Length: 180
DNA sequence: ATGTACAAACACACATCAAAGGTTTATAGATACATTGAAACTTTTATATACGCGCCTTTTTTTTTT
Image (cartoon, rainbow, N blue to C red; front, top):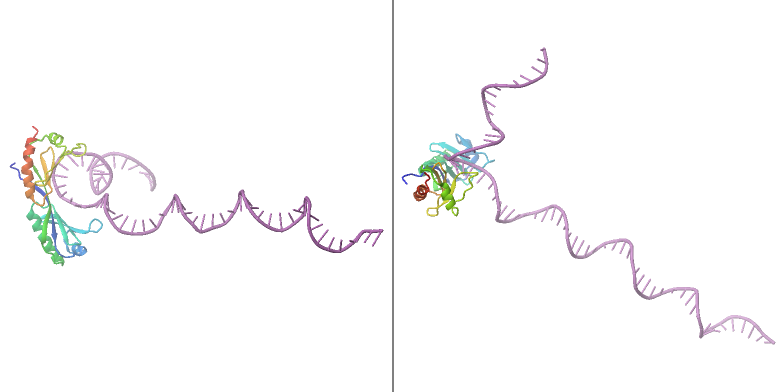
């Protein structure tokens, strides 16, 4: 392989443990996008770490755009601190990353036609809307989006580690299906 | 001599029975709504990937009165 699956989004859940006044949360924040007509969750974008989070009336926050487990975790801790400054005793309790989506590259042109045709059972293709293949692995259970540019979009894991394992499993397939 | 009010036949005029049928309507078939709970349904996003299209937004061209 020799290629790290480069994460582009990490979505995580944080139980602040309080019924947050989403109106006051929006009011006391600096740049927060909350109005009920789209969702029941204040969405805040913090530039450091730059993450976008929706926090619900349950006080549960789901965070996206992180580049690491620690980007999301530190961002969520900052989010809880911001909520506490707002006035609600937010606390980092029973945190869990619900999604780790990444894009990386293997850089060798691929016979995507070969894979999809011979892995019709596993991968399906209708190249007249979107030129990417969809592949599944159960161990680890990662779904992977493949495009001729070599871009690999690995999704379906709470951790980047399942991303890494399925990438170490799928890059050999890619090189096998490398078009030249 | 002598036929007359009176009541029996004796076959019949008279009140009665009975089949048929419109009309009314519960009564039921079927009817069209009225309930509601329930699951089949919507949403973010970002995230790149590689598209348009229309609409944000703007530059260049286009058009009536004194």
